[PDB]
Image (cartoon, rainbow, N blue to C red):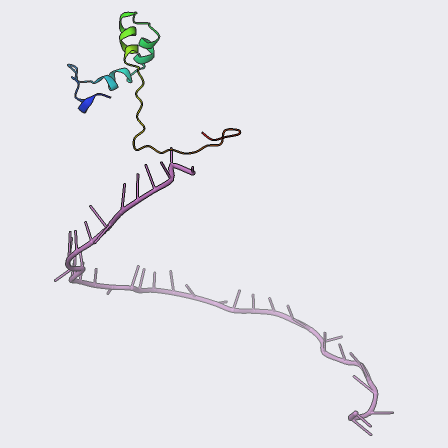
Length: 67
RNA sequence: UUAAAGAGUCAACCCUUUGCUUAUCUUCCCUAUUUAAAU
């Protein structure tokens, strides 16, 4: 996700969602088969972001109590 | 218990034409008999 999903297309015309999900280069980079230069930068983007506004909330039984 | 919430509304010509048609052997055969008073 990026604001307005603008980005910049390649010379043939591709975005990251198409590039990383074409022929499984995501696992080829996450493992580190392309080096440790494209491995730290990609892992830097994997950060959590909490937001609960306008989401369903349901009670589930967990032994003695609820969650 | 993916809990809680929400107006789909409005309008319309389906019209026109038409040759179904010719022929034909259903044949042979046969034991229905046996009683009893009107309530």
